[PDB]
Image (cartoon, coloured by chain):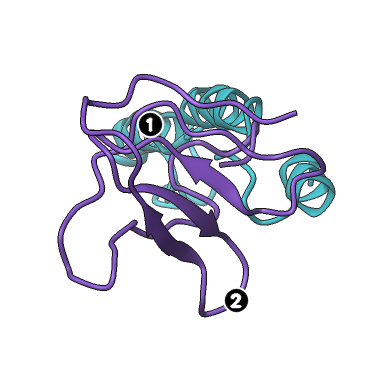
Chain colours: A purple, B cyan
Amino acid sequence: WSLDMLSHPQDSMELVHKQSKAVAVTSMSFPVGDVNNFVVGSEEGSVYTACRHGSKAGISEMFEGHQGPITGIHCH
Amino acid sequence: AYMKRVEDVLGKGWENHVEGQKLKQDGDSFRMKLNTQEIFDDWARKVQQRNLGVSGRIFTIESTR
């Protein structure tokens, strides 16, 4: 969204994995530099890296190393 | 002319922009306070009222007095 126009999203798409199931995100975070490869804290596990530009935008891969539902993420 | 100045400055997405919506509303209401066809209506009625017996008064080319 621009900070000017807000009646319509500037650029917008969903976020689904290889399967067409939803990605209940929770506190995503862009890494340093805005390389558009923001990490997404999903609902539980299946934390993803997701791109914004190109046809490959969105969900890149799933890594699971915990089973409790995710609450946050951060980069540095 | 000011409105076209505004949108040429602010792009065609212009009311979507934070201020353009405001200036749009204001120019519109200001425009609604300028549709003067009522003046011609009522005044045309007064003219018609006078026209009933005045506008073609040549009926007495050299009227008595």
> Label 2 is placed on what type of residue?
Gly
Q: Chain of mark 2?
A: A
Q: Residues within 10 Å of mark 1 (few under 14, many from 20)?
A: few
In this rendering, the answer to whether B37 lies above or below A49 is above
Seen at 57% across and 39% down, the residue is: A5
- In this orientation, which residue lies closer to the viewer: A41 or B15? A41
In this rendering, the answer to whether A35 lies above or below B22 is below
Which residue carries the number 1 mark?
Answer: B38
| Foreground disc of the pair 1, 2 | 2
Q: Position of residue B5 (x, y in %)?
A: 83, 46
- In this orientation, which residue lies closer to the viewer: B61 or B52? B52
Q: Residues within 10 Å of mark 2 (few under 14, many from 20)?
A: few
Calculate the distance from the C-alpha at mark 1 to the C-alpha at mark 2. Answer: 58 Å
> Label 1 is placed on what type of residue?
Glu
Which residue carries the number 2 mark?
Answer: A54
Q: Outermost residue toward the left?
A: A21
Give yes or no for contact between labels 1 and 2 (Cβ–Cβ under 8 Å).
Answer: no
**Which image quadrant is residue B8 in?**
bottom right
**Quadrant including the N terminus of chain A:** top right
Q: Position of residue B27 (x, y in %)?
A: 60, 29
Q: Outermost residue toward the bottom?
A: A55
**Which image quadrant is residue B17 in?**
top right
Say whether residue B56 is left or right of residue B25: left
Q: Position of residue A14 (x, y in %)?
A: 33, 57
